[PDB]
Length: 119
Image 1 (cartoon, rainbow, N blue to C red):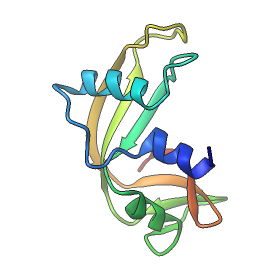
Image 2: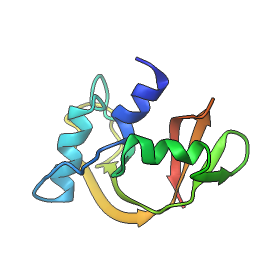
Image 3: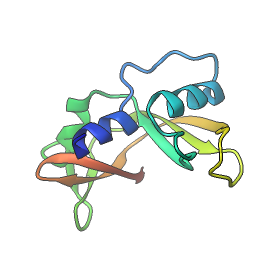
């Protein structure tokens, strides 16, 4: 898996996957996307924009933010999932919120490789 593919798998959900509520969205998506084995990932943001929309952050669609970090020009629909309690052992239960925010990602060679935070 390329670092780019890992970024899409972990952080890109577009169009947004339908779910009954955000807790269920998080529970389903964290598992579907490979983030609950072998341990529960503590937190993860899904960005609801295309790979192309996010990739431009690394170039004309974003701005330098120190080191290899870039801030997006655009605000994006986001869902943020945070693990209930503190244990890495499954079962992995999540809570979640949604927002519309600019984002700060790490780029390498013009492509996204990590999600840093919402701005």
